Image 1: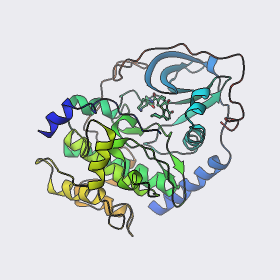
Image 2: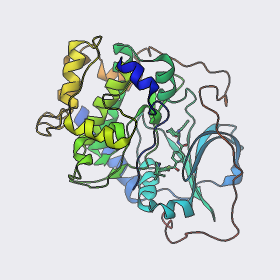
Image 3: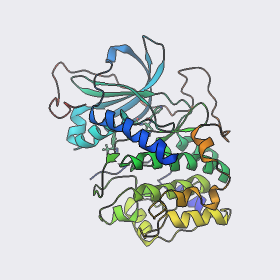
Image 4: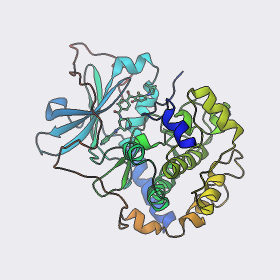
Length: 20
Length: 337
Ligand SMILES: CC1(C)CCCN[C@H]1c1ccc(O)c(C(=O)c2ccc(C(=O)N[C@@H]3CCCNC[C@H]3NC(=O)c3ccncc3)cc2)c1F
């Protein structure tokens, strides 16, 4: 399930804005 | 009366915008209690104002680190904007000042914690729950954009929940006052509009795309575009194929197809009727916009609060003693702060 794919991802924590 | 409220708010804004408040407090006026968040330049701490006993959130930024990462102008944007605005769902700046090492912004303490924390723990919000939050963002963005302000970092991490269960937007480091177009590649990967990713030159419409991302994330429990590396997220965003969970109502789905619209001539918030295309959409039929503004709507969720200065709605972070150098750092760069 998409939910399961999300929970197993590295993107469920506090997300940082980007820089270059 | 919307147009009227907005003309008055603009007058108020511009006076503070053209003559910013400076140096309205000092570090020794505050007892530092606990870190409520961090970033690469510093941290936000719970503090206590000694002369009133009031609690605040104090953002501390290291001037040399700001300079090293070339965010001087963005930092000046943040403070100048925050001191000038005034809206129920925008965190209120109370004081600002600087010393030899650091910049400081003291704002209202919003004790209910980040939307992000509740959203992850609970899993997802019901449609009425997400709609109640969404309404507040719609109004906030109507206010900000009327002032030529673009926010550019909408996400649950930046939406704090107050004692009454209402939102307060925080972290204006990418907010900018701009007429017409701008080009900075900034934002959070999951929330970037396709036109940012494609180095196009963009406007206030990227905030309306981000609203679509937020609403989706609040209602699904995960964002419409995610992957383990940002480049893969960007590829998903530009392709623009969104799938909706089966539990999304057809009205929600319809709203989101109009917000998550790659085509700027078709994206809601960006058409002839502006924000009214959003406000009058069927997903929002039960929403009383004036009641939201006046905070008279009953919040579907109110966080536990056990005394003033309690931080149980926040994660724990490593603490670090503030050090003030005996030599002034980066005086010229931050003269206006
Ligand atoms: C370093 C870059 C430029 C590039 C990488 C991404 N971050 C960027 C970035 C841009 C501007 C910045 O000021 C910073 C910071 O160093 C910084 C330092 C501290 C904070 C901070 O702690 N903010 C907290 C936690 C992050 C999520 N947003 C909520 C915010 N909390 C609050 O503002 C808050 C207010 C009132 N009551 C309770 C809490 C945010 C940013 C920053 F890290």
